[PDB]
Image (cartoon, coloured by chain):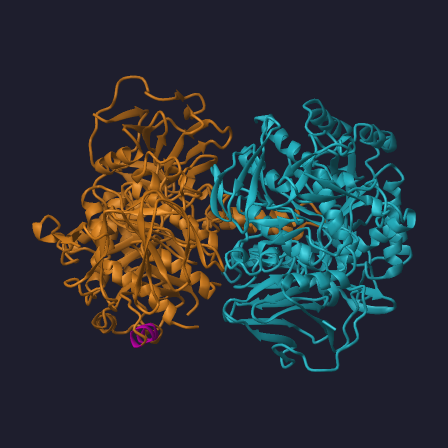
Chain colours: A cyan, B orange
Amino acid sequence: AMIRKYRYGAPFDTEALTEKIETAEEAFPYGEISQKEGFAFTYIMDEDDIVYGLGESNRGINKRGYCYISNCTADPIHTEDKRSLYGAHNFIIVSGKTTFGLFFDYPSKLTFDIGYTRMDTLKVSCENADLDIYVIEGENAYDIVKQFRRVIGRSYIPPKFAFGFGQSRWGYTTKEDFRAVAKGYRENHIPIDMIYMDIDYMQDFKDFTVNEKNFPDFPEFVKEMKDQELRLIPIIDAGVKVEKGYEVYEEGVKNNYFCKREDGSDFVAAVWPGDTHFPDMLNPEARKWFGDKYRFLIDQGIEGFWNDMNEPAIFYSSEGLAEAKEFAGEFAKDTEGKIHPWAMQAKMKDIVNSPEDYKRFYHNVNGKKIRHDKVHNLFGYNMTRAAGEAFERIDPEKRFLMFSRSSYIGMHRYGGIWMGDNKSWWSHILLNLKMLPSLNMCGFMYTGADLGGDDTTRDLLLRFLALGVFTPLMRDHAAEENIEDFRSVINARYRLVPYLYSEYMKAALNDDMYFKPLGFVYPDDKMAIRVEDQLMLGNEIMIAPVYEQNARGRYVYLPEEMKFIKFMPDGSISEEVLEKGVHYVDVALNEVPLFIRSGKCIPVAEAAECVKDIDTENMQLIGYEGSSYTLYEDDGIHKDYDKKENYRVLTK
Amino acid sequence: AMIRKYRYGAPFDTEALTEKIETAEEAFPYGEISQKEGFAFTYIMDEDDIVYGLGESNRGINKRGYCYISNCTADPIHTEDKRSLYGAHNFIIVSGKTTFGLFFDYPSKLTFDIGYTRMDTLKVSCENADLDIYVIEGENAYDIVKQFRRVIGRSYIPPKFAFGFGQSRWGYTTKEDFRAVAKGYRENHIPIDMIYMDIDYMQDFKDFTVNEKNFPDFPEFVKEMKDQELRLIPIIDAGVKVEKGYEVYEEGVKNNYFCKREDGSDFVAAVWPGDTHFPDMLNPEARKWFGDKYRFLIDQGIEGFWNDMNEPAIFYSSEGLAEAKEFAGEFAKDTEGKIHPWAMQAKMKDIVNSPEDYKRFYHNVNGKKIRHDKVHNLFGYNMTRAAGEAFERIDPEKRFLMFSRSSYIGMHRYGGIWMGDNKSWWSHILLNLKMLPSLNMCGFMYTGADLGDTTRDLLLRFLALGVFTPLMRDHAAEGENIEDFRSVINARYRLVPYLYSEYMKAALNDDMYFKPLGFVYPDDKMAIRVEDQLMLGNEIMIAPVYEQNARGRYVYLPEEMKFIKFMPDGSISEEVLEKGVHYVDVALNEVPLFIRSGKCIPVAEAAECVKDIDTENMQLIGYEGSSYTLYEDDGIHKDYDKKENYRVLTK
């Protein structure tokens, strides 16, 4: 009796929540609901109200003052004005004198006008009034989030090695490229556990193949790598190549597993392999077939995968390619200047990720033909759901590394999310920082981010990693000076793996958040609730990364007394007490900073070069003498979660 | 004596400098010069070294750790990976243990690799060793700046009305559109002095025409607005439309005033009007004629212009257009998947503002046909030089508002510049703030920015910056509690006497309007690294909030100051804040600032136009014992020398 479900029309089932809620047959408690123009919820905000949520969305922790459209989009630019990223996360919480959470359970384009049109007005709208709205109430936002976290079911948990460092690069192809990196890191003694394989390892980008000529005994090569504690983490894309004699393709065609055109034919969408077909992720039979395929690589020693282009992205369709050729031909033989160069340009952008192409193909959902656009936001969800179920069939008791580009609430149980770009910008450290608590709100905990890019200067990479240190996914993956600064930073990471791991485990198992906004921890502190460039982690620290070029430090607000801790290259740990108030603090490039809360402590291992070798048996306790910390640890591999003996109390 | 000139090859005379200084004969006094790859300058910086300058460029005040290409581009998205904005201001100061300044007098593509490739390495390189390098010695950066400000000639001084608020909409096209701005502002008591006219008022986009249909009795309409103290500010564009019987064009052809191709034919480039030619801005004769054409508008009661598109922007040439259709052809007829879409797409982008186009036209300069690419950064500057020089012929006694998009050092004598793009971003408020000191260093002090969909909160914070920037406009595209809007604009008007006073004093003394905390607090290791606060003249520090949804921000104070706030109700709050790190509260409808220890400034009652500002009885805000020299003139003419312009105010 603090959670209500309001149903309108005939909502498609997303299986986002795992707890059942009775339909409310009373009045919608807040705002106006209107069905004149599709569906709209309109609400007038108090001046001080903060709006939390929307997981993977643009701008800040407080969403007030802009427009967000939930419409999973393969856009990779990410300017302030972008309305849509890769995530459809329709959770929000109004935080003011009146406080409530709303989850709009809806698979299609959802529109969040949060102060955009009129500063005082919140307006959520969509084309058809076929959705469920959950209303969550409580003390405050954190309490609201915590109930929500309880109904959407438990968050995905990676194996412990996923808490190491990873490196990848679009362009790695041959055994020698991967041999070259193991050598780089291991011989310069940079810690690391994972090496990503970008698309090039396949046989002509064909899903679930390895390049036969570059990889003649993959399992022997996989084992080669596993013997130096390097786990090869290969990519899988939404598109299956159209190739005669390609087995996946042939079973896809034969068993009616790909999405279909209205006319009955298998829909074609050009991606990296050229012409592909999309597996029908909403069809549970097609989902099992595709999930199962991952066995092919699991059977060769592979322990982690990443799914990509699953919005799904489309460079162009057959219809659109043809449409645009006809235009071009018309442009080509204009001389009366009737067809303009920017019209010809505009037709060319318009065939990439075209709303019209998302209306040309269909899902067969338990017998029901649905057009993709009606449910577009669930695709990548289900692609990840597919793999996550295949894992439970092969070995229910084993955790695999899995993370996806596209997501919808409900996926949070089957994998994590990675934030990527086609650009390396200082502003993106801040962006990625602010996104963190918001992902946590909607259940996405194993997340990190990328520096697309060759305008990665040394310092950008250094500060970028110094945030990455605290993000559960931490890698250096891009397209392809002073080596020892890079090492000191990965050292800091590995010194922190045990505590970070423990905080994540305690959080995941308790339906609690990993990263929190200062607002959640200090809700009555009117300064704290406005800080967006600092986060609280677990119940013990606060992070405040440096994100400005040329900066020798930054400003901070401490909502309470804390120990300013830093990891110094020499392996030392500088420690200083700072009163509640505002401070400027020195943080050099190669230095890694966090603040530990009054009467808290955290354990700190010596640096180790891979996760299995971290000496967790006798760690140092940094923080305040007298304080306790509960350390969680298990085998890091399997699902033996509810043991008293996974918890140990440490005292300073 | 403190400035030496190092010449290599046969440099085009850019006329950036008003001073003649002899060619130095010794070897180059700092770093290694290499003429291996063309021309290169290479200097190893100390870790503590800071790098200043470049005026209108990307990123922060300390330029270290990125790459900047001096190459005026009409590129419109101003993301932080971009290495070329509109300006081209080749003036840098290295500041640390070894301090010195460098002006690279080179009219074409110049690359500043400042810590980018390699962090301690400063490398400025260009294709051809044909350029003058000015080396400038000083005790510090501020010093070095002030000497450079001396040799490049005094900065453009604007009419005082140019110090009011201004407004515009790309879209405005009828007498009724403009009357609705007038009524909306004057009825609601929002101060305002200018209405900008964007391109729609021209006859089919033609320079020095007015829309026959929408403005039949134009001088009359200008008088209509002037009487309400609204000065109309029409835009002018580099490209002159190709049109039979359009006199600007007819004259331009007959007299060879346009940029020609190699075969002597007038170059074609498509802009707003479709086919246009570009006035040969480097031909002193063509400049003479182009500038004179402004008389058409001056004679009608117009007192200010802005030049846009003067990079010059090219949507496409005739030649690039045929290449595109060639390629459209190939694409449309491909069946084997030979030509992919991404390639078709690229050829289209590639024909906009093309490198290859700028190798397709020439300037005739004292009988030398010079390829445009080799003097590219000079075009907009010379377009503005033309207008400015024409003003002295057309109405010699009188100051005109004039400001342009693309520039090059030298331009600063003839007009201001404005920064905009097509995006409404928060980070841009900071970009704009950071650019100013840099622009003051290169002579450009009449500057300001645009927010080219803008939210109410963004507008308000944008405007609390523009309060202090000599150019302050809300110029958008298209066309809740307005008391907030008025409050911010009111602070502007209340502060007009002071900012104009500091501008004039700075203009007349080759000093700076805005300075980095560092120039004022050189011995304060904290202060020299501040980038989001500015000193203005000798009395105040500014610090705008540039974060969405914020109630305030952190500031550093290098000395005791009064924290002042212009208040919605019209009051002025005051707090004495000691030296140190603070957090300060600033609501969206509050305009912050800091008066320095030992100092005071004057503030007027809010007034609704620059004319009616009551500058007799004003209050002094600041510290109880200090005095301020207020510079004030008629704000119209060019009599700056008089003892009458100054009067010491004492608190």
Identify the image quadrant of residue B218.
bottom left
Give the residue at x 40% y 20%: B32
Give the residue at x 83% y 57%: A258
- Residue closest to the far front: A626
- Determine whether, in the image, residue B46 is placed left or right of residue A405: left
- Residue closest to the far top: B26
Quarter containing the N terminus of chain A: bottom right
Q: Vertically, is B28 above or below A247?
A: above
- Determine whether, in the image, residue B387 is placed left or right of residue A396: left
Task: Please say whether residue A234 is one of the residues in the magenta stretch.
Answer: no
Q: Nearer the viewer, residue B549 or B307?
A: B549
Q: Nearer the viewer, residue A364 or B118?
A: B118
Q: Vertically, is B370 above or below A150?
A: above
Q: Is residue A331 visible?
A: no
- Residue closest to the far left: B643
Q: Where is residue A145? Give x, y as percent.
A: 68, 62
Q: Where is residue A334? Give x, y as percent.
A: 54, 58
Span shown in magenta: B179-187
Q: Is residue A404 visible?
A: yes
Task: Please say whether residue B186 is one of the residues in the magenta stretch.
Answer: yes
Q: Nearer the viewer, residue B281 or A450?
A: A450
Q: Where is residue B328? Give x, y as percent.
A: 59, 51
